[PDB]
Length: 49
Length: 49
Image (cartoon, rainbow over all chains, first blue to last red; front, side, top):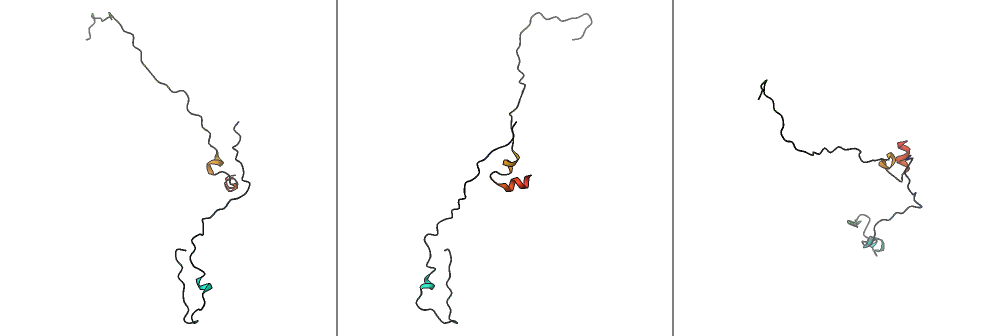
């Protein structure tokens, strides 16, 4: 009789994501010396990062 | 030709060998229902039962 099919169950889980390397200066506004006025506020455009 | 008093009898013969090819059996196959849905997952087994 062919009663079943078998498979080895996994021991643990493995999750790998690609490198975040070659980062953009997202901390430029964080380490900036002086900002502008509250009405003069600057908007940092972050694209392809 | 067709006549009442006429008859044809063979004066010589020949031995001919022909070929008929007759299949007997086919390939034995068995398909699993669970592995056909997916393996290594309990979602296929609970929804399949």
